[PDB]
Image (cartoon, rainbow, N blue to C red; front, side, top):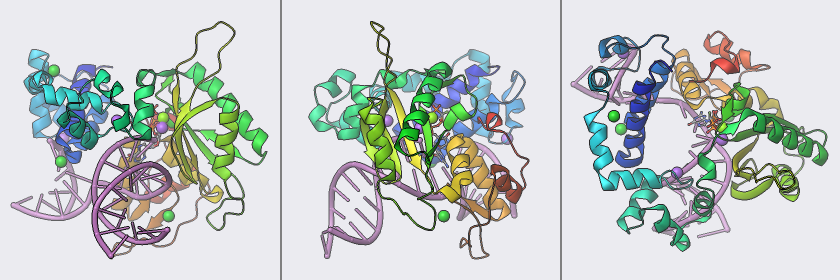
Length: 326
DNA sequence: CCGAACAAGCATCAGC
DNA sequence: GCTGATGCTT
DNA sequence: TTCGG
Ligand SMILES: Nc1nc2c(ncn2[C@H]2C[C@H](O)[C@@H](COP(=O)(O)OP(=O)(O)[C@H](F)P(=O)(O)O)O2)c(=O)[nH]1
Ligand SMILES: [Cl-]
Ligand SMILES: [Cl-]
Ligand SMILES: [Cl-]
Ligand SMILES: [Mg+2]
Ligand code: NA
Ligand code: NA
Ligand code: NA
């Protein structure tokens, strides 16, 4: 982390604009700049040097000059002093509490972890579970635990139906030594873009992982997206593992390669890649890549039989998962 | 100077 | 009930 | 907040 000081500052700024200002474009601006600086292979010596990077403009450049001279940013130090900003920012760290609910809670004087705990009746289901495991969800997952969780998920999915295919994606598939959560892509041959032959395809998997006490809680759940909580089982007299966020996405089997591209990320990589696709004349989502007309209407899906087909279409060299950690 | 800035599933609410 | 917009999250 | 045209 050559420029860890600068990238923390920018991330803290991005969080401020998102949670407090509700200014999504400033937030994306700071996050993109933090990501382009994180991969820049030199120790930045001036904001002018940084401004050579795309995504670093005038305003971020002078902020980087301030930080390099003084080690601090006055704007951030003030935001830290402000109670309402500190409280809104804190509350948004509970899963299911966003900037709107956080500001509304603060209006009602709900302002701290203890405030939340004494007001659970005021939370929806998701927020209640986010508060429940608030400490656990901020711990990272060593890759060695991701490997145990993977082995549980793939083996339980195998017992439901041998034709399911479960792929762990996210930072794990990018080779990260620790992950914030576990992301599981699910396919089954009965579910394609053309037909859904079996019902409750995701349900059955959720139910099987609940019954072996791997999945502990549910945050949200539909026919194709499960968001919930899991916990590794511990040995006799060992202390429990933390609970962990798990996301499961059932994708049409014929659309796996778009699905695994989407779910491997990163989120910023996805944004950068889908943006460039537009410039090249395509739109990419988790299902398809399609040409755009002159009007701006998506045409029919183009054929895809590997991740790299998608890169080819928009004329990018293939980048292995490991190199998509923007 | 001005428009664009990735794409979408689920929970929840308002309005009919 | 349904539709559509918003919040929140991936 | 930054970029491209
Ligand atoms: N197009 C688009 N895709 C998004 C977005 N947010 C998450 N994704 C994608 C890609 C992720 O890696 C993936 C999982 O979402 P994630 O929040 O688990 O991200 P991640 O890459 O796994 C993190 F590094 P970690 O989980 O380890 O803290 O889903 C988004 O805003 N737009
Ligand atoms: Cl904005
Ligand atoms: Cl600072
Ligand atoms: Cl599509
Ligand atoms: Mg993840
Ligand atoms: Na720049
Ligand atoms: Na939150
Ligand atoms: Na996730």
